[PDB]
Image (cartoon, coloured by chain):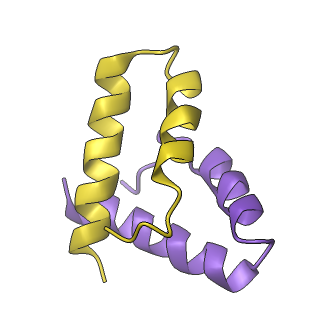
Chain colours: A purple, B yellow
Amino acid sequence: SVDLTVPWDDIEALLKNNFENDQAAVRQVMERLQKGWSLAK
Amino acid sequence: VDLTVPWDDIEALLKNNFENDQAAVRQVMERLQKGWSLAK
């Protein structure tokens, strides 16, 4: 049931660029966005 | 809502992905930001 139709992979590529290729930051933001998506619906 | 997250750039990406559908972009931006503020 985990959401797959938001373009998560494209969002991740955007975030990796924005955060200067900081993997830890990308992981933190992707985790919270996807957790939040589930909690908000 | 943490403004270090590049919400405007995410919106531009969604607009392309959803064929410029305003309603879809709104739906997704609403839920992403509601979820961000809820989630820790």
Percent coordinates x, y for residue B31 in the rendering: 27, 49
Residue at 70% over, 70% down: A19
Asked whether, in this view, residue B5 is left or right of residue A22, the answer is left
Residue at 65% over, 61% down:
A15
- Tell me which corner region of the image, top left, top right, bottom left or bottom right, holds residue B33: bottom left
Which residue lies at the image location 52% right of the left edge and 14% below the top edge? B19
State the image coordinates of residue B27 (x, y, percent, origin top left): 27, 34
Residue A22 to residue B35: above or below: below
Residue A16 placement: quadrant? bottom right
Where does residue B12 sit, x and y in percent of width and height?
Answer: 55, 33
Q: Quadrant of the N terminus of chain A?
A: bottom left
- In the rendered structure, the answer to whether residue B12 lies left or right of residue A1 reads right
Residue A38 visible (yes or no): no
Up-down: is A6 above or below A25? above
Identify the residue at image location x=36%, y=70%. Answer: A35
**Left or right for A3, reference B23:** right
Considering every residue shown, the one lying at the far right of the view is: A21
User: Does the rendering let one see residue B34?
Assistant: yes
The number of numbered discs placed on residues in the rendered structure image is: 0
Front one among A31 and B13: B13
Q: Is residue A40 above or below residue B16?
A: below
Q: Position of residue A37 (x, y in %)?
A: 32, 58
The answer to which of A16 and B5 lies nearer the viewer is: B5
